[PDB]
Image (tube, rainbow, N blue to C red):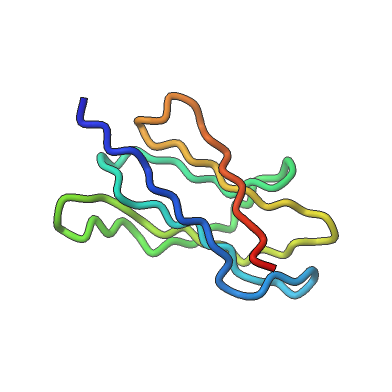
Length: 100
């Protein structure tokens, strides 16, 4: 019990173009408690170069953080995002999108 599931909103910040290094923003919120894992993960390559906007639980009754990277979609790369809050018994590798 007490299982606030992660509400994902995984968006492109900048207009996605190959070579022209862009910005991929996995943002998860709505959930609690703190125990969540979000590795950005391509076809089979983990992006270790992750910056965040830190834990901001809005000091209300929520829990969240923004987890962004400067992604470069070379040729036919499909960038995706691990989602594994404590509620998720299995890590859901939610693929991002391609707005364009």
